[PDB]
Amino acid sequence: QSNISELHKILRKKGISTEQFELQNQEREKLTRELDKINIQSDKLTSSIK
Amino acid sequence: MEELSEGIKELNDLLIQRKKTLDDLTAQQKNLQDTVTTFETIISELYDVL
Image 1 (tube, rainbow over the protein chains, first blue to last red):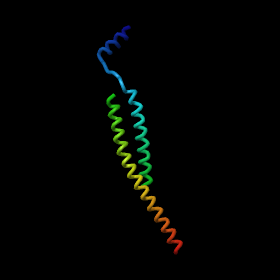
Image 2: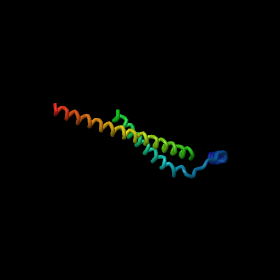
Image 3: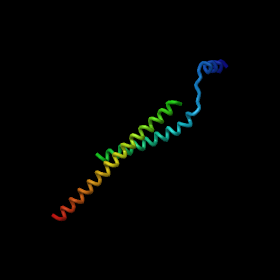
Image 4: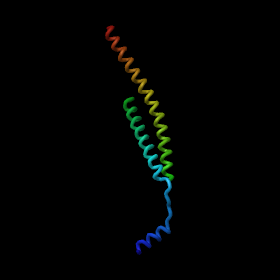
């Protein structure tokens, strides 16, 4: 109970919230994968061009 | 939640720039391939005529 009360006090001291992190996390992952593919293609093309 | 959107925008901008670079590289590689095949066929014809 003492630990529960201390955690309640900490939650009274600090806020923070979450609304759309998980929704756009997938979009960020997709964008990162697309950029990785594009970068790999660019590096391969540069080596082939050299 | 905001760094997520900032990173998404940065990834999109870098992807656009790398896509322009990739298009330029594709043009250069196609020109190089055309030049190489042109020189190879000219060399083959010259040796046959020789």
